[PDB]
Length: 185
Image 1 (tube, rainbow, N blue to C red):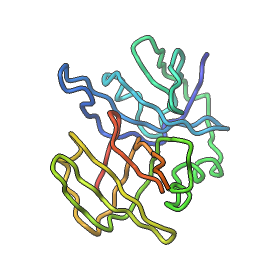
Image 2: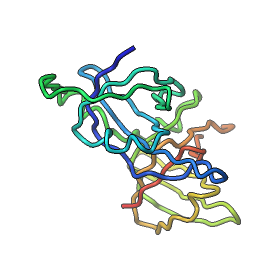
Image 3: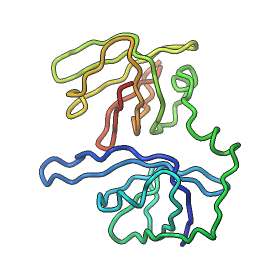
């Protein structure tokens, strides 16, 4: 089951389940051939997921195109003599923000990552709506719950992690879900 990977980046840690204060973080890792987004539900594993570190992983769970790391998952250290080298081809193709017009072109559901410019902001009750826009188009980001407490003004840019892309009658939409994360630039 063993995958040896290089850690590209990792977010800060945050609460996704409030009642028992369970925390997680997000990470991106790579083999020579593939980039993987990772959901890490054991916070004590933070040091192990440091940028440029080489690690070995087995007994992960696969769900919605993420690898999920739980206590039954083996995460081990790899010796220096592995000399892992990731082709820059793979790593640039890594963190590419999709164009909004293709996002509003999908009917299949997915979970998206990317840096988007904040065009407009509207608050409706327990809901915050961001309109995002690029050279190809625009669409709304629907935020409910915990992520509404992070402040973001017009003109700012947002690094979104694990947003749900949902098709509408007609148009697409992005919505916060339980593992979503926002970073403001």
